[PDB]
Length: 269
Ligand SMILES: O=C(Nc1nccs1)[C@@H](c1ncn2c1CCC2)N1Cc2c(cc(C#Cc3ccc(CN4CCC(CO)CC4)cc3)cc2C(F)(F)F)C1=O
Image 1 (cartoon, rainbow, N blue to C red):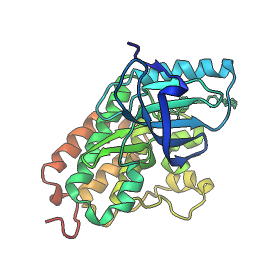
Image 2 (cartoon, rainbow, N blue to C red; image 1 turned 90 degrees about the horizontal axis):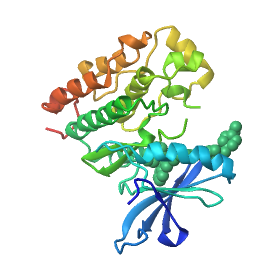
Image 3 (cartoon, rainbow, N blue to C red; image 1 turned 90 degrees about the vertical axis):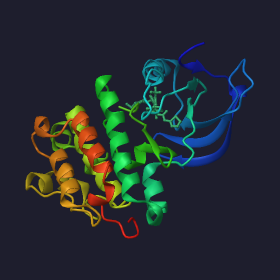
């Protein structure tokens, strides 16, 4: 019945580890919902630290919000298991994170895929804005691949990635939908460089000073200047001058109609 299912351990199992971050470990698994027969492929995130009943109330309040997300380009929380180390269940995104996907499939990715991913990520971020949800950690690592044609945003349920942060976030810990636009621009740069490292080899402590001098990430080799200009707009110092997600959907959708006019990839005729 319930929007957020409160799971028993007997209902699911871990099959394969997928990755670990600072706060938890993600597994591919299987869930048979209590009272049902069907086997659902899931991702299971187990938190690194054990939590108290008090801490679990803060988790539950956020988990209900995460279960309320309903958009084709945003991952929804399906369930929670209140084990000592809490476990969080979503539908499995079988192709993993988009960062790894573009690094591992670089030779078989054309302009149409890249521009459609930019549209879809903008659509998911626009829904979050409509829901008054600030992501605060948008990056290619936090976009998942359902199919090569269908990506979804995740890991916004977490409220230091200095190299993805808007200048105002670095200087004053101000986070808004418009600082998410800055991070969107970095995410697009990641895609267009097939998962390269932003501000590579430069210490995080230097980034605010580089940005204050007007320096920005470089134009990727595949990008026409028209695409680079969208990234540049996302990195304007005045937050309210940056594009809105709705505007980014329009502009990337136009480019996706003639994708080889906007990204130049060898073999992508
Ligand atoms: O579930 C998540 N990812 C998954 N991937 C695959 C399967 S599930 C992602 C996620 N974010 C948005 N979405 C998702 C999935 C669907 C959309 N989330 C939601 C998520 C996560 C984490 C926590 C946590 C935590 C936590 C809290 C307190 C302490 C103790 N320490 C607090 C700090 C304090 C220090 O002062 C001391 C006490 C510890 C941990 C909660 C949630 C949420 F929202 F469910 F309540 C997390 O990662």
